Image: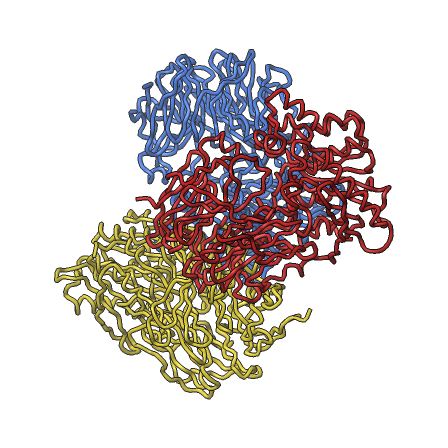
Chain colours: A yellow, B blue, C red
Amino acid sequence: TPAPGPDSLLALAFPSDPQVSPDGKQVAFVLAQIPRYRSGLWLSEGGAARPLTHAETGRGDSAPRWSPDGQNLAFVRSAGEVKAALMLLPLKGGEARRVTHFKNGVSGPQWSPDGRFIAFTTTPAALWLYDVEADKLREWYAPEIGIGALSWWPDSRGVLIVQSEDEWQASQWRQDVYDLPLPTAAAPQKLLDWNSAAHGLAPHPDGQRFALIGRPAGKGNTEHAHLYLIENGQHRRLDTGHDHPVGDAVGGDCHVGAFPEGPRWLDGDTLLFSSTVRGSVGLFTAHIGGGVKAYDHDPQGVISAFTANEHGVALIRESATRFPEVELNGQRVTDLHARFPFPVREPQRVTFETELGEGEGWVLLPEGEQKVPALLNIHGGPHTDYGHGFTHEFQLMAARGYGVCYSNPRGSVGYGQAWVDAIYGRWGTVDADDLLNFFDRCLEAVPRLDAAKTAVMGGSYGGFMTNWITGHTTRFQAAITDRCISNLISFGGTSDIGLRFWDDELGLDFSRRADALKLWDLSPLQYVENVKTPTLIVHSVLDHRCPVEQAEQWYAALHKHQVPVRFVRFPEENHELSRSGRPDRRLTRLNEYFAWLERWL
Amino acid sequence: PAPGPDSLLALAFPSDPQVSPDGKQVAFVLAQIRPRYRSGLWLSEGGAARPLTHAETGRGDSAPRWSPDGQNLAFVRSAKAALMLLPLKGGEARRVTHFKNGVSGPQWSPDGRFIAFTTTAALWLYDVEADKLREWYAPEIGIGALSWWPDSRGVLIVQSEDEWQASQWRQDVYDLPLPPQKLLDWNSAAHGLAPHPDGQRFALIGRPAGKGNTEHAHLYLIENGQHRRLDTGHDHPVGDAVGGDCHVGAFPEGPRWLDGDTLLFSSTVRGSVGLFTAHIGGGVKAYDHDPQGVISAFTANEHGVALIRESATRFPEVELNGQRVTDLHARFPFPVREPQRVTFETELGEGEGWVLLPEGEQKVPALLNIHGGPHTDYGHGFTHEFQLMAARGYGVCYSNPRGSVGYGQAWVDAIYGRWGTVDADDLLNFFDRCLEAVPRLDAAKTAVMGGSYGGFMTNWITGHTTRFQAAITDRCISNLISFGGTSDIGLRFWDDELGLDFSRRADALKLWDLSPLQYVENVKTPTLIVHSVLDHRCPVEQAEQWYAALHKHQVPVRFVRFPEENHELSRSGRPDRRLTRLNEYFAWLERWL
Amino acid sequence: APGPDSLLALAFPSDPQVSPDGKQVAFVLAQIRPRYRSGLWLSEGGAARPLTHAETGRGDSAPRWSPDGQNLAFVRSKAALMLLPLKGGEARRVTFKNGVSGPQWSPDGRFIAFTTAALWLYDVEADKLREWYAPEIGIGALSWWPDSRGVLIVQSEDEWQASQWRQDVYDLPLPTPQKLLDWNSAAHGLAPHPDGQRFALIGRPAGKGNTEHAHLYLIENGQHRRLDTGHDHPVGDAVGGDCHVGAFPEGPRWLDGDTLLFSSTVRGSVGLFTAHIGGGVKAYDHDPQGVISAFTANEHGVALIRESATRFPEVELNGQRVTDLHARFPFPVREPQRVTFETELGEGEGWVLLPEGEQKVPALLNIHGGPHTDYGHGFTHEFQLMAARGYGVCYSNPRGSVGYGQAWVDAIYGRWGTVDADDLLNFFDRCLEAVPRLDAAKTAVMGGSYGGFMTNWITGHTTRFQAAITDRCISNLISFGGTSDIGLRFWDDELGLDFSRRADALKLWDLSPLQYVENVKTPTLIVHSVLDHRCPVEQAEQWYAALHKHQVPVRFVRFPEENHELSRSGRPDRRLTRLNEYFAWLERWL
């Protein structure tokens, strides 16, 4: 195997959207491949998956959807002149046929269970309806604000949709569920007064009840997302006795494309869903009268996407040492980890003590026995987990001679609601303690880690924490702050989530004098005069979530203090690989990371 | 019907009044007609000026420079930017340079052998007799002011040592002979190099090291590395720092030696700009100073003087040796009205302001306008915006609070380190005296508005009193902390203006206590927010914070985000930004009064 | 009342390719100012289903079955060779800046031959390409030997022989060409015998000009014997019809070692026939009232396209219709009635298509081009549309037509404007007698190419017609000889005259309708393409200028698009505008 560099990424192909066939015997999925990445449809009937489409221009093909009779695949095509067109491909032979002709394209196609219709959105994006037998199209519903989740009733009489009433409620993450019948020209009638976060609609097979993922209106958005059964405007929690959130919230950098996680009824009593547990993501079943049981939970693995019906299940699975692979009914149908171009190593667990119990993290070491630099990596969120996702960046760091230290401080999401709530209103206290305590225990437990060549780095909240830590201790020899936050006041006015984020996470309103002062005392920029650590700053110019003004303030302050500093301003926004298939941003980012580490460690 | 913003399109804008070496002619630039403005050269030998070039594409022609023999005009043409030579006695202009990125700032050598200019920025040199071009000097940081020695042996140049000194606005003067040695240890702000006729000494505009850039810019004679102030007994800054919105293009103000003992310069005095002479042996004398007028640009030699002149009631006109040579005020499409003076008292003496009323006798809404800077003056510049406001039925109230620049150094220093105290007092005190002195002003239909520092002050005032019925904040500042990190002047601006460093904890808290956003919870006044998305001086994050805060408080608010940067009319000739800005101003005032 | 827009309701089939096992048929269908695009369709016995879908360019054409029956090669549009697995999957692009044409699989499935003009060869198993042969002059017909050892190709020696339609047959083995037949004449449609040595061709031996019927000839060691003996009719479809868009294969196919299947034009019809090595011709599928325009065959099955004067072209597989294209015709079709006339060579025939009702209707004499083609039992949308708009359409096969024996063709040799004009006016007079609904006071004459020559000739020799429409006309036979891309050979074959010879040129001038233009009084619409290489526009310019000088009402439509633009690019604008001009002129003068 050759010498690993950032270029190792280009050897990888990225799977997504594992769609099981209605009869449960096949899986169709998306694979992004090589320079620009483009995606095509792949198919497996139990054996090694085979390519079904091959794109040479544009972004490629995505969103495969089986017709209920199992004979056709609907999907979205992005070519040289087409933004995103709905296609129909007969599986028994022939070429795909273009069905829609929109300048701006379409997204999110869903067959009706009877195969008579395909719903999709196009431009707020309006909901359209394709009549399959009549080959006609018609605008179904044009919302004033926009449509969130969508699912057909099992009898194909209409769809349930999630939407807000105004921009203010959407900014506050408050939504309701509506019933929308097929048009006989017709308006949607409200079905549930939720006034809260809701997605992942799972209509019960009885045609009346339905499940959703979210939280009731009473609790803030730091509350674990849970499963709720809805019946005649009432709600009943289904994942009772399960102090863990629904969905995958574990880190990993090999997710390109759509990763469906919609709950699915295996029968009238059983609801299948995914859940994050201590750095892992497993499949579980909820019973219509309550109680969670494990369905497919490896405490050392991550199930990042799944589809299911009464006849089969398809999913994508990964671990800290295994690249994502597609499965059909427990049989791996891809050989994607074999493409990983250098050997992966096994992490070692290192724990630390907190007043709420033992916390955990991991150390990934390189080969050999010599002393190696120690890199403390901090995940964002902050309510996510490090753990058993596959992280090409971490394996590459170890392959280049660095010890990677990454943990789940208080504020992480997989260790119970109380672990999340520990940092509420006081970022920079017990979370910073846990991160520095964890790192100290790494230096003690692993003597190979060189205590004289250490660095701290993280993204988003991890960038906030990198700025906070370097402003409160000079112990680190290098720092890399990515998509950072430095000034909590200006963030509240500039971020597209600034109006609600600090209220949910800290109970503070930047537009209120007393709250603003508290936000300033929580801002790493107040303590910037103490920073002595050479810092690399990475940020997108057009970032709407963490505006680049956050990074500009940190750069200007360090520059004024004559602290060695380097500011990489990307013209591409984050997640550019998924957006256009161009890996340039990821490659340049990794290059800047290692160049900075090489100079100072 | 009442005139609207479209009245702007009736105007033509003069700039760069260049007197000929023999003092008998003046060449200048005129920008005239959304419809787009283009510039061409005009010429007058004493009578009505005539067009000399006619551009139909691009931005047009600029920077006319007389050849020493008086037979040719050099200028810059954008049809990017080419150096042209036009023989004045007959013929067509000839293109001389072939650069992709263009040229800027041409200056003939006094002997007529060379023309110096910059290009990317490197300094280049054109040999006139040889018709050859050649790179003179490629600085690492950049070149500021530039002037030829009188014997054409070389040039004096202003430049900094590093980017940090440039960020701190500290510069030195260098000697660069024909194809550089440090000539003056200045380590401070310097421009307007005016070489003495003796070939050894030279004067400059600026300030010595010690006090920050809030100190009045003055004239300094340099001799063998030593400096002595020349404009003594004159507690006023050099240059035009008076408001006005009919200045499009370049306005030269370089001091000029009328003889071996007399240096001609312009100076701002109590809302006016006049010409003065500083004498090598002696103080300052008035040369051409109307306390009710503004001389915005001038060129001079031993034989003649050319300038641009304006007042609060007179559109800018070009003059040659005291004779008006343009007819530009005649183009103003509606009658202009005369302001009345209203005074207010402070512990530093009497302050002054003005009220411009509409025709008639009925009550009219009262608009308090606040100038930016803050170290500039309102007063006797021509302001089309103010005349248009009065023509549409509004009483315009504009004053010079403490912090303004034309009333002595102490008037400037009163606000140092404490914006939002005595400056805000002076503005509301002045406005109260307006309501008292002018009964036509409607005390129940008032609005407050301003740009840059005036936008900071609009945000500050509405956060400390609900008295105003409407507010318009333009290119505002709302968060002094984030400004320090985002502004292209943020590293030095608060240090000079407030003695505060945003990167230091104790100073940052003081900056937050001076930030209008801390008090935003008190704002009840409907506010229009105007800002350019690409603003580098006042980043748009300043306006985004004010909008989001008012919107969260459910205060009526409107946020106009311009894709065009400020001064787009001078930049590309497109008046769309100014027209749209005025439309948004009046639509908001019509909605709330 | 229906107008020219009715054309846009139609979809046009072409290239019916039977599968090697004879159980399937793949063909091309072009369907919808709106533009026609073509895609591949497939039927295994039932209603055909679409197999490819093109949204840009002209579309897909030339489907060719893999010998194993699992893949389809085809051309996609400049023009790329594609391979589509029929049991599932997507098409793969296989090849060039200038595109491809005429793909043919080797019988063993190891190669695909094509042109791009150089001959190229695609190695299927190796997925490699290689130039096979780059001729100096060009390649004509091409067919693989049954053992896939090489190809037979038709070529001329120089440009002069090519202009004179003189060709030979060459043998080209697979690379790592020798002449096979001293033909020195016209040849195409190579049909290699299954024995790997002999082969048949369509054409004519040297001696008589190209007015001689094309026949079938079996080749053995440089010797030739006519195979379709006792059959005084030419090989191939030479019957008029305006619903043929795309390629219509007519290559003869050996059904066994003794039987060669071929098509032939007989009295306005085209049927399938078999020629036997040991004896005469027998009918295989010949309806005297129908037209088989294209066919492919093997030892296991046959696919074809069939039509009649009252039935739009449909695709068939082993006698079963697999398309429903006639159902798309947007107005009722009417049936023509036969009207005969007498000549010294026997009875001639024509047809009259009337409008609905019983009132008097104008009479439009239409003259087909060629001149050695037939009117009759092809489907003609233009004629049906004319009848739907109130016109009686009269169209016949005068002497010079091709389906009534060699003597019928030879009657006009060297003397256009004599017996052919007589037969046309004799037929038209019999129409007025036999069909009292035809209005003798509201008559018009019209035709294309040779029919335009004849429209010009007739109106220069009689004023009886109230209107005239001359299309792609010929007016000056002298200048035609020098300007036409066939001018060097056409008059020599058709008239025995050489325009570059003084005596012949005078004879050509006496045959030129422009000599007699001073007699024209009939208002004439002139239709011509500016870029026409076969009938240069100078032919129409002379007729327009002459009629205009005589102050005869005249209108000159100059199309920027060449003829057959619908087949060329899929744009029907030329055909729609042409029909609009036709009816506007007829509406003005009746």
Residue at 44 percent of width and 84 percent of height: A270
Q: Is residue A461 visible?
A: yes
Residue furthest to the left: A369
Nearer to us in this view, B19 or A245: A245
Q: Is residue A490 visible?
A: no
Residues B375 and C112: in front is C112
Give the position of the N terminus of chain A as an image quadrant: bottom left
- Residue C350 to residue A68: above or below: above
Q: Which residue is at a point 57% across and 31% down the rendered structure image?
A: C489
Of the 4 image quadrants, the one containing the C terminus of chain A is bottom left
Percent coordinates x, y for residue A104 in the rendering: 55, 55
Left or right: residue B177 compared with residue B374: left
Residue C194 placement: quadrant? bottom left
A563 sits to left or right of A209: left
Instruction: Name the spot of residue A268 as percent of width and height, x first.
Output: 48, 85
Q: Which residue is drawn at the image coordinates 40% and 56% (left, top)?
A: A38
The residue sitting at 67% across, 35% down in the picture is C412
